[PDB]
Image (spheres, rainbow, N blue to C red):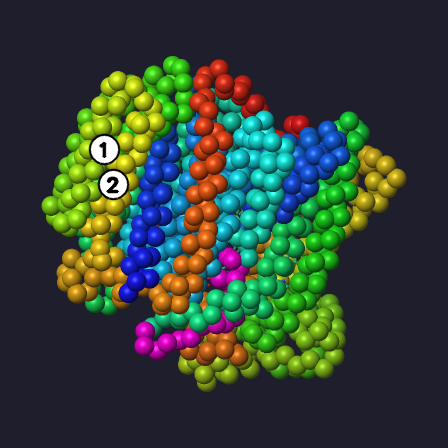
Amino acid sequence: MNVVDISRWQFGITTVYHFIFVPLTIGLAPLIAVMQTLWVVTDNPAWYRLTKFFGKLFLINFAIGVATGIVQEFQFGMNWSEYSRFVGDVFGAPLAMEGLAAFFFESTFIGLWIFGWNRLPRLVHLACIWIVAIAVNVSAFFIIAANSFMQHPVGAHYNPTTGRAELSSIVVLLTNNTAQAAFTHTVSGALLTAGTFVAAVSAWWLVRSSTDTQAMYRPATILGCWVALAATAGLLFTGDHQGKLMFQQQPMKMASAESLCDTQTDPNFSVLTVGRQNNCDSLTRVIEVPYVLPFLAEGRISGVTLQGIRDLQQEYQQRFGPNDYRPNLFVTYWSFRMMIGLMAIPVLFALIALWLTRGGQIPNQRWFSWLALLTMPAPFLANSAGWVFTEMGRQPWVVVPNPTGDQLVRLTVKAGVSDHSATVVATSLLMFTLVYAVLAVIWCWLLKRYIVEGP
Amino acid sequence: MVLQELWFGVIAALFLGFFILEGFDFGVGMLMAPFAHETHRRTALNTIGPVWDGNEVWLITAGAAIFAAFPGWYATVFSALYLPLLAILFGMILRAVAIEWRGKIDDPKWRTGADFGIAAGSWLPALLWGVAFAILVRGLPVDANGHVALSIPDVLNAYTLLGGLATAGLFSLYGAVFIALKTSGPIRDDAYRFAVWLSLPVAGLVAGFGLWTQLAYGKDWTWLVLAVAGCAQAAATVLVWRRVSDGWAFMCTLIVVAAVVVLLFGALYPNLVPSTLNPQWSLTIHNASSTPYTLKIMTWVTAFFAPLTVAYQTWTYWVFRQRISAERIPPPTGLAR
Ligand SMILES: CC(C)=CCC/C(C)=C\CC/C(C)=C\CC/C(C)=C/CC/C(C)=C/CC/C(C)=C/CC/C(C)=C\CC/C(C)=C\CC/C(C)=C\CC1=C(C)C(=O)c2ccccc2C1=O
Ligand code: HDD
Ligand code: HEB
Ligand code: HEB
């Protein structure tokens, strides 16, 4: 492949590895704070063991979560030097502000929480995990707002004197509609990942114990299932806020989730589509469910018109010049079925687990124990698919032009790449992939060893 | 203008804090292997246990500050120095997971792999960061278009290699006096044993690299910084032969590490990426900075959180200020392989 394609894969594979542990870290930190808070108030030793058990698993995930984010901090200047200069006046502020407002807090107080069990007071030690639980959300907000500037640039001017986008208002950049919608959606997505993780592990031990520990994992199962259900409700509301934003900001991405080819009124959402989806003209649709795209685009079931990919292709050529504005249809289409479809397993598991644990009942079915294990990777993969559709859906724009903002504030992926050779980026891409793959296997093995071991 | 010059020192201070805090963190990592030549390795590791994450963020904050304040500086050094920075990230990644996962599994082979990750995350950053800063002071072949086209001799030369060894040796001495202050007993005595052996050879590397930077790239006012470094190094050299003080010994070594950062940044002024082909094409703090509004907006955030960051980070070291010995180390609570 060429330099641009290799650089795209590298920024992709490494940061996808990063978002394997990030959603667990964001959601689990408040959960452990809840368990620790209940132990202080209720003086229940069952919650203390839950804090030590799930806290142990959090530290394993937290350590590899930090490691996978180190490269991303300097990755912008290594492989996207041209992109870094263009938006450095705007894009660098959220990255730097998160360093002193969220990264310094969640990394300093995490050490106090680990080594301060017998040194710090109970009230002070409890606040240490709450600060970490808050700082991870603060870090998510700033890192999403910077990415939301790519999706919907606001508060910036082109300043044709120099070839870079310049910040005009920091309030507008932080209060972007895309930033707030994506932040609340990712946090809701992170809560589902940890809520399912806590529920699945606790439910797995309930069957194992039946075939007190039962007293301990039962409250965690109830807490985990309700958080997952609450996160599912949040994902629907925030997911409804995001689709609407997608419609008026990135019409290409809205039709990318449909593989729409012509401008039709009230299109039908197709569950499955055969073929490699190159040209799109010959696409075959299976199980077309209506009243879905109209409701996600403008919030109404009928009367919504969506521009096709083909129609938008020539429209973009008349304003931005001759270019291939067609994203990867096969990847974006199936990564979107994946984000959505992967709600049934977590939601399905939560509903069942609550039904089997009603009135103090302890489940003992063997299939229920196996259901929890398969439910664990569902939110992890759904979170990965959600951000993939966001990044592949905006191709080939690294900075999507704002329809209601400055037209000149935009950049393509090819024009934002650095001037490296095909062998230098490939060597870094190869060494990044194997190192993260080995750590991912160790991370998965470490969690399995401690889950079966228990307290 | 003012904000442009002010943010040059803020980024230097962030790198100053990174070298002061992560300096002994690297020194501990490269001193674990000679300690065995298991209990001593865990005692030294627990000294930087609850502070290694916070210490590291200073590099992350410094890297992100450069991105926000000087977009041209961020996109030039990290683009040109792709290979030396690649190995820096490789080590850091291993150390970020080896420290936490070392005690998870109780198995001699498991700890052997964890020790390699800590060593990789302590040797490469100690050596390559000194080379990376020496490259900036020496300069890069930057043309008018902003490209670099880096070559092999522009990275591995006499000046850059000396800087890498000096910083790595200084960090090893920095970690030697840090363990002697954070530990007591036989482990503390071993820290002074390596400190004496790392006193004279390290002093020659720091003095040789400091004099070379001063005579080739230093300014008139930077002579005082080098004089303080010499005085601090001589004071730190004599404070280990006789262990009169642990804190003074650590404080004197702290000044030596701090003076190197000031000397490197003092010579790297006002240029950010000096051009070896034409000094007019060099990247400065004026043609590669952000707008005053961006620097202004970041000034209020920095003036509120950076002083606040030092408030609890210092308190974090105060919480764990008690020295740890071999008898204070808890038994290994690691699962069987
Ligand atoms: C009810 C139910 C099962 C619903 C879901 C099933 C469904 C409806 C559809 C999915 C099934 C089908 C037919 C296709 C999959 C759809 C699809 C391609 C989704 C995107 C792929 C995706 C989200 C993968 C998840 C990756 C993941 C978490 C793997 C496990 C974690 C581990 C240990 C390693 C993964 C990291 C790795 C080695 C590679 C990551 C590659 C990925 C996923 C993204 C990066 C990436 C991709 C995918 C590009 O296409 C690309 C194209 C051009 C330039 C750059 C890139 C790029 O960087
Ligand atoms: C929505 C959440 C989210 C997203 C989209 C990202 N991150 Fe992240 N990042 C986290 C959420 C997060 C976190 C959850 O806050 C982590 C994981 C564990 C941790 O300590 O912080 C983290 C850690 C983390 C660290 C470790 C800092 C430390 O604690 O020592 C760095 C340097 C980064 N990230 C940088 C990035 C960059 C440069 C990204 C974009 C390319 C990025 N992250 C995407
Ligand atoms: C800081 C901000 C940011 C962020 C946050 C992010 C976050 C993220 N991400 Fe990103 N990216 C970016 C910035 C970013 N990003 C960029 C700039 C780029 C370049 C452009 C392209 O290449 O596309 C990318 C690219 C990319 C990719 C590739 C695509 C292509 O190329 O085609 C991928 C796959 C991804 C994923 C991802 C994820 C999963 C996530 C979650 C974590 N990404
Ligand atoms: C947890 C897991 C998950 C889930 C479950 C989900 C579920 C869902 N979802 Fe999601 N997402 C996600 C994860 C997710 N998700 C992500 C990660 C993302 C990226 C970030 C943001 O926010 O953007 C998204 C994104 C997104 C969006 C936007 C796109 C763009 O902008 O690019 C939308 C519209 C949606 C919808 C939705 C829905 C409707 C649903 C229902 C089914 N999402």
Q: Which image quarter: residue B80? A: bottom left
Upstream in sequence: badge 1 or badge 2: 1
Residue farthest toward the left in the current orientation of the protein: B215
Tag of residue B337? none
Ligand 4 occupies quarter: bottom right
User: Could you tell me which residue is drawn at 45 percent across and 57 percent down?
Assistant: B301
Q: Is residue A185 visible?
A: yes
Q: Which image quarter: residue B112? A: top left
Report the side of A311 relative to B248 (left or right): right
Give SS at disc 2.
Answer: helix
Crowd band around label 2 with a 10 angstrom C-alpha radius: few (<14), some (14–19), many (20+)? many
User: Residue B74, relative to residue A438: is it above or below?
Assistant: below
Residue B264, image x and y in percent?
23, 47
What is the three-letter code of the residue carrying label 1?
Ala
What is the three-letter code of the residue carrying label 2?
Ala
Residue A138, image x and y in percent?
55, 53
User: Residue A272, relative to residue A14: is it above or below?
Assistant: below
Q: Disc 2 marks which residue?
A: B259
User: Residue A48, relative to residue A173: is it above or below?
Assistant: above
Disc 1, disc 2: CB below 8 Å? yes
Q: Quadrant of the image for the N terminus of chain A?
A: bottom left
Chain to which the residue tagged by mark 1 belongs: B
User: Could you tell me which residue is drawn at 75 percent across and 31 percent down?
Assistant: A44
Report the side of A165 relative to A179 (left or right): left
User: Could you tell me which residue is drawn at 40 percent across and 63 percent down?
Assistant: B296
What stretch of residues is rendered in magenta? A142-162
Q: Disc 1 marks which residue?
A: B232
